[PDB]
Image 1 (cartoon, rainbow over the protein chains, first blue to last red):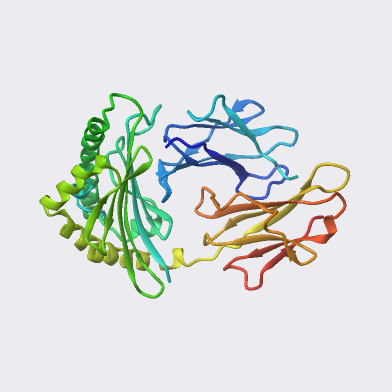
Image 2: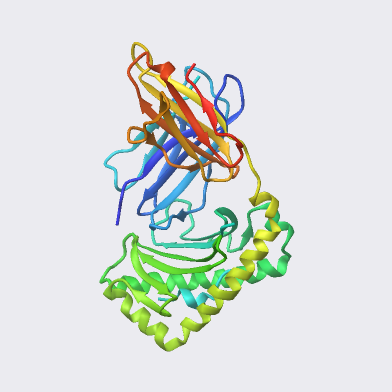
Amino acid sequence: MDLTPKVQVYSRFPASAGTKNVLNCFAAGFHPPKISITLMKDGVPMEGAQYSDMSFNDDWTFQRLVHADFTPSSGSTYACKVEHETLKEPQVYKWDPEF
Amino acid sequence: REVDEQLLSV
Amino acid sequence: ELHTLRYIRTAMTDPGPGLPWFVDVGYVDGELFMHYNSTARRAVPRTEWIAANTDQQYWDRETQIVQGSEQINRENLDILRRRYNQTGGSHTVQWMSGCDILEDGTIRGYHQAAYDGRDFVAFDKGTMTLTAAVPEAVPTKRKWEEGGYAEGLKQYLEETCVEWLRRYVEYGKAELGRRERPEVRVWGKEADGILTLSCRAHGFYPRPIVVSWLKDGAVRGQDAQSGGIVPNGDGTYHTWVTIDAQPGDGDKYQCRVEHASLPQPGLYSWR
């Protein structure tokens, strides 16, 4: 039955100024499989996003990874915006750059 | 390889 | 060494926007190696090692089998809908199949389906029967008792599955057995000193990993919050563990990373 998506947002490499990277948003533990997951920079959808094909775990709950190439600029806000039936409103998960 | 289709029929 | 083949099928009525209603993804030792969906209508390789050790006969074969599988699962959605008294709406059939060659050398086999995210049927090789989890699966069990399906699957799980798993493992032995060291970062956040401490391992392979925090040597795990293990795009893995500390206790804490690519566990502090 319909349970909520658990969402993390992280980068491929430990992030540094001016240095190419990949931003990741992974959602798991959810049902039904229809889900909207959008990587964003300062409120704007980011461009090169790739979405994994629909897959699930042994407890039958679904998962999807979304990733885009990017170069993090300091003082921007990066986030992952998620829609799902289990959620009243869109949830926005902020990326912590860690530099 | 995958299995014969028929084995997924309900 | 533990090896696994998994085939993971999702048929859905409401995918939705721009997405395929049927997908099938194959995994070897957790690594995505084949893919089909109802838009491409082509079974496709997903690692370089499987692409190099198969010809077009193999992918023509897998395509027809999975194309028929797609049609079987179109029918499945319509049949289960009726048995559940449903009309229209958002529904899914899930099918998992595969096998394990364990470290002790034993074979395990899986064949199970779920409807709308709930157990529907499972194969029980011990007793050699299809178990129905809910009354809506009893007609399926009936179907398998008559159609002579159970023997055809025994062949698959005990022979075909394991034989190909052994092949695949062989095709990509170096890739599957590789080691990628994590880049680890420690970061601290909030208030006066240093409240929350983060430990992130970036880009490790294989998947197993233990990341823990140590307050003056003491594992504070009932206290640690973990993200579990999540994937990067490139086939490597990611994990973060946080721990809450009184501000200015920063110097007391150490992050410990146990992983197959590290001969000694890695030890990290907050700067």
